[PDB]
Image (cartoon, rainbow, N blue to C red; front, side, top):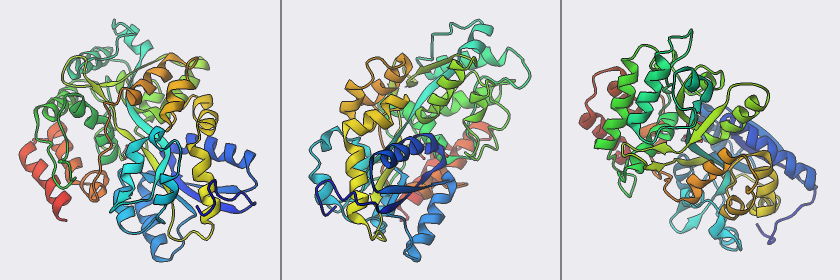
Length: 403
Ligand SMILES: OC[C@@H]1O[C@H](O[C@@H]2[C@@H](O)[C@H](CO)O[C@@H]2O)[C@H](O)[C@H]1O
């Protein structure tokens, strides 16, 4: 940071991250604070509050020592000078090639590198094995295609049980919707953006299949749980956690809660990679938060001590693997989970297999995550409305390129 492994001298370091990653953030900070003189003062911020909080703090130069941001948000923040240039420190890491590359790439602008992985968050398919058995489905057969996803959701919908639906769609969360829907497109070998991130390529047969799948469930009695049309992103993981949804895309960072509920006598959870339109094709969204040292830090060496510590396979095993969470370190993924719950090892295989993507655009929030983004309207038109996929896609590109 200035020293190789930074300075551990009893400095209080501030770290900001977001509510969806709260369980993993707690584990990381608890472990750091138990093993260092330095202490991290953790703030966990609601997902939708980070843009305005970071923007406001940038203007009053009160950004924290360590800022973690959604990997889709980082390219913009890094372009605005939110982060201190740590190119030489990242480039000195012996194990740089083991670190989740999408998170480093998110923070790469003009040869400068600003970020490392903080918490990996990947999208997977989860299903309720109890509802599957009740519906006459094989409880171990996750969907291998978007068609099979529809069939399984429809059999759970046909149970006609109070508050039970086949699937659930985060209708008003552009962010949840990229996370949940992009992988089906990538699984098929299609793209959602051009290489620059300046154009949307969403008007494709795989995206149309995915939207038509959710349209079918929208037009099925009990197809999509109540709340799907209004879901802001604040509650989208709750209906499945509550045992009310047959099958849906889901964050790996929320699965440990499900595995725990199951150990405590709750319903049994299936996990599989998100499938393509094409039988047996799979992908994921290589998301989560990357972290950098803010432009406002007066403890760069102490912040670097945290950044350095977390990249090590030791810390990655302690804070991720030993807590049943997916690590940001591929060497940790390949070595530290040999006796983990098979569903954890299945989740890790969607990183190791290499079929996932991290979308990179300076305009990503404005085009995708933002409330009433062109992407949110595109999905809404296609699922609950009349879609014009060509027109809606061009609305996304007009934000991506303008400017
Ligand atoms: O934001 C894009 C990726 O999706 C996941 O985050 C989601 C939020 O956008 C949504 C609103 O909270 O909750 C989801 O967990 C990944 O963490 C992001 O990289």
